[PDB]
Image 1 (tube, rainbow over the protein chains, first blue to last red):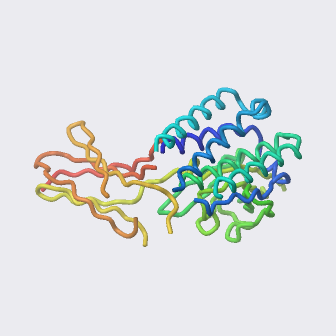
Image 2 (image 1 turned 135 degrees about the horizontal axis):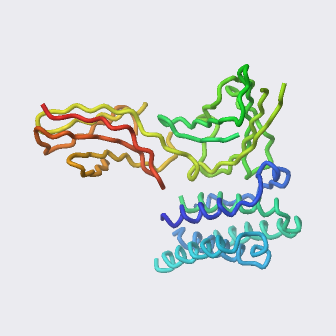
Image 3 (image 1 turned 180 degrees about the horizontal axis):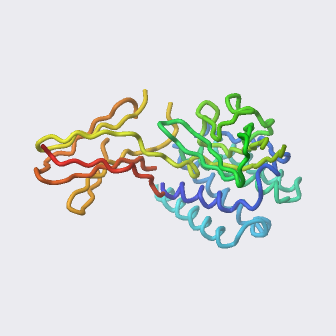
Length: 127
Length: 180
């Protein structure tokens, strides 16, 4: 809701470095937007994001206070949805992200690339 | 460089200010790309070697779902460049529409000037103010849009402000009238 907006604002604030300096690391992750009944796919989406930004690697890449705020927003959204093929496509998508970070050795730029990609997939899936 | 990205009459306008002042007008070139694909920086055609300190990105920035990355090159014989990134749903400031009012015996016609797709979830707010109290009207956007503030009284100054609401808002200057 304003929860989606808050989530995006927190991701924006988490940025550590200039995106211009990271252009070389950009990568088409092929987010399967055609998957966006759909609530369960959204929940799986958000849960995967929660897990992605919960690794020891995410903890080293991002500000801890913003991470708490971000976690709080994802948790609240999942609560709101719980209450209420595709999922496999989302899972593969997050596998592609995870592999990307590995190959890149979790570089500062690879992390900006993933942060910006998550903003995109989150805004697409929740609009 | 300092950058501002503003929606004005539904046109996305990127503007910038420089730290120092060139005695002959600076020439600018604006290039941008997005993060989601490894595409080359692209020059914005109506913003290539220009003396204007803004660029209309309406036809370029079609989506609210991309991280936009900009590079501004300037020739002030000093060559400088500045980069920035934008997420439109967050960074875009929504400037208020132009409007007119006409006071009638017991009501005010408020006419808001919109132009004749659209990517933002915006609401129009019409503020009515009198005797130190402000009331918000949110009418249920293309062309002139009329809204009537009714049940008003003589010998009373009313001040109207309008704005678009998406965050902090940017309100129009006041237009005020007593009823005839």
